[PDB]
Length: 398
View 1 (cartoon, rainbow, N blue to C red):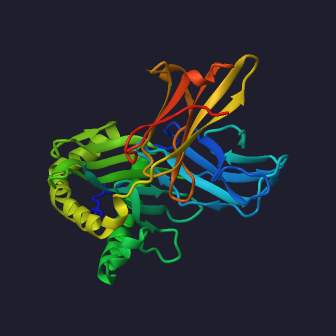
View 2 (view 1 turned 90 degrees about the horizontal axis):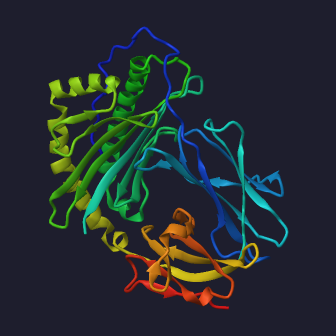
View 3 (view 1 turned 90 degrees about the vertical axis):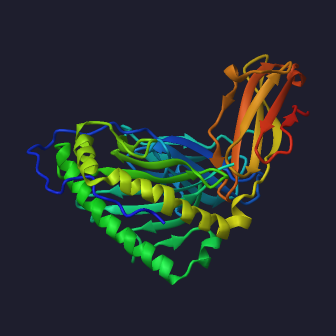
């Protein structure tokens, strides 16, 4: 159960100033890949994973031979610890030897759209809420969202852009909670929504910004609990336009304000004793709810799926070749892939991609290294996953 938020601003706006402000935007990183190994003629799923962008508004199109693919599905949007957003776009497809596919992304951080082609060669716990409020002048009321996570597993979601906004279960095990729980969570969310709507208007003034620009307020609120049931860390962090604004310090008593706008909120919260209110929520209410969700999600939550791995071989200009170590279908996402030459790790020359979702709940990752042609048998790939009884060792097999 997410906390009921206290407004960041004093209420009254103004701050005689317009067209005086705006922060850096973050460029999207893109990966295009199939869910399953690509076999010509076999239906598969093609993914376009877009991460690290800010603001949240983004346009994604998937292309087949240069033409827009009409039926492209989009996952709900989320954001990570660094405040940057991520989303997965996917479409069904049956790959062929000669059909080219690509993913095109339009985002304010870039001058023109970016097209990325599909290259098909060869023991604690935490309850955290990720909150997003995005103003959108002209296009309507601000979009407000509350997303809940038990150990990085999304389990509840409230989105104001739904037809009649309501908290929804995102894991089957939350279906146990009765009507009173959902009703109370839904009403608290709508109350929180109003708080952020007012803060959006107020911070617009604190930063002397134009009235027609879209801005974002984000929050990460929650608790990390040790196996002994004791609070390990409490979180109450805010960002404005993707940059730190204010956060409760580890002492659960004082605040760290990132700029002068935030000092106004800090002073306001110190006088009202907001830190004490959060400390109580973080050490009590948050921990109690986390225990209740862990109980209900028991049989589902702890589970792990070890990576199925293998090595692929690819030509490089002249006497060099690339060995690519693949780790597929694993869960959770945490994993380590390394290449060794003579029992020694070659981290400083490996090429790797950020771990990514297959779209079926599992993850994928690969690490590669360039080696002399004919020396492939001198290298070994090591896959360390928490689901592995023992770290895996693989070699290229011809």
